[PDB]
Amino acid sequence: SSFSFGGFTFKRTSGSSVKKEEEVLTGNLQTLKIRVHEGYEEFTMVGRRATAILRKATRRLIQLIVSGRDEQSIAEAIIVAMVFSQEDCMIKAVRGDLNFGSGLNPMHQLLRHFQKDAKVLFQNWGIESIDNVMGMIGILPDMTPSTEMSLRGIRVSKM
Image (cartoon, rainbow, N blue to C red):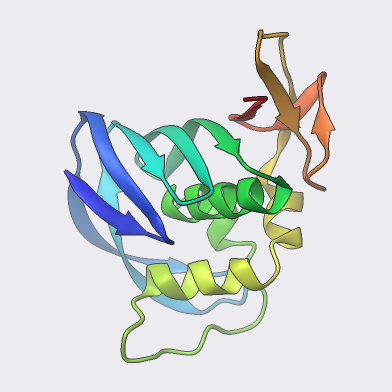
């Protein structure tokens, strides 16, 4: 109902999920046992420097809106959401092997990997054209703003 992930507090505002153990193959053909969230869920994510709303389904990010203090704050939230979505394109953007600590499950391994360098994640996520929505703007895989295109399913609040 409320939990923390990647430094953000997630509050479920709609839906539900169940957790199912599934093996997945990373971009480096490493096998991870991840606890997959199955179901449709809406969440508020609250961090110290950014807030976001996320709508997602099983291994699928549907919508993310991010409001952040600066560009780096926004990127952090986007990475967290993209990892939390458990999308195949995220799993396959992993480069090299992930090392297997006490204190780390596979979801936190994924997160630490992409926090280190998210270029491949962003490059493989996908982009789309957007509509003009008052108070909203797109953000590109290079983290620059656009009024015309954005990362798939992702928008930035100007406030």
